Image (spheres, coloured by chain):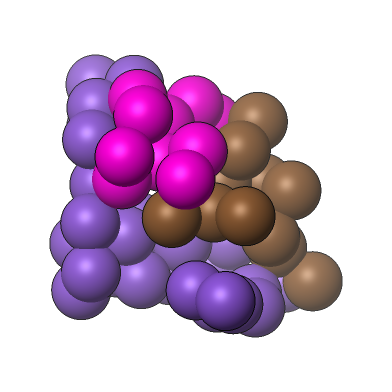
Chain colours: A purple, B brown
Amino acid sequence: MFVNQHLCGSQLVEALYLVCGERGFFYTPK
Amino acid sequence: GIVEQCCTSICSLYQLENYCN
């Protein structure tokens, strides 16, 4: 399942988007 | 942060949820 993979760049942002749903999220690559 | 935990190493659902508002 994608949550247990390497997720990089836009795939990481899209995973956050799908998992977090109405909560929204923060993406801080630092 | 999230890149180290989910891109450079293997992600988890906890790691993603830790960045939900």
Q: Decide if residue A10 is on the left or right side of residue B2.
A: left
Q: Measured along the vertical axis of the image, is residue A26 above or below residue A11?
A: below
| Up-down relation of residue A29 to residue B15 (above or below) | below
Most foreground residue, A12 or A22:
A12
Along the horizontal axis of the image, is A11 left or right of A23? left
Residue A22 shows up from this direction: no
Residue at x 24% of width, y 27% of height = A5
Q: Main secondary structure of the magenta part?
A: helix
Furthest residue in direction right, as rendered: B21
Residue at image coords 54%, 54%: B2
Where residue B6 appears, as percent x and y from the top left, is 41, 41
Residue A12: in magenta span: no
Which residue is rendered at x = 31% and y = 39% of the image? Answer: B8
- The quadrant of the picture occupied by the N terminus of chain A is top left
Residue A24 in the figure: left or right of residue B11: right
**Which stretch is magenta?**
B4-13
Examine the rendered structure and indicate whether residue B2 appears above or below residue B10: below
Q: Quadrant of residue A9?
A: bottom left
Residue A15 in view, yes or no: yes
Spot occupied by residue B3 in the image (x, y as percentages of width and height): 43, 55
Residue B13 falls in which quadrant of the image?
A: top right
Quadrant where the C terminus of chain A is found in the figure: bottom right
For this rendering, which residue is in front, A27 or B4? B4
The x, y position of residue A2, in whole percent, is 24, 32
Q: Is residue B1 left or right of residue B13?
A: right
Q: Position of residue B17 (x, y in %)?
A: 67, 46
Residue B5 lies in the magenta-colored region: yes
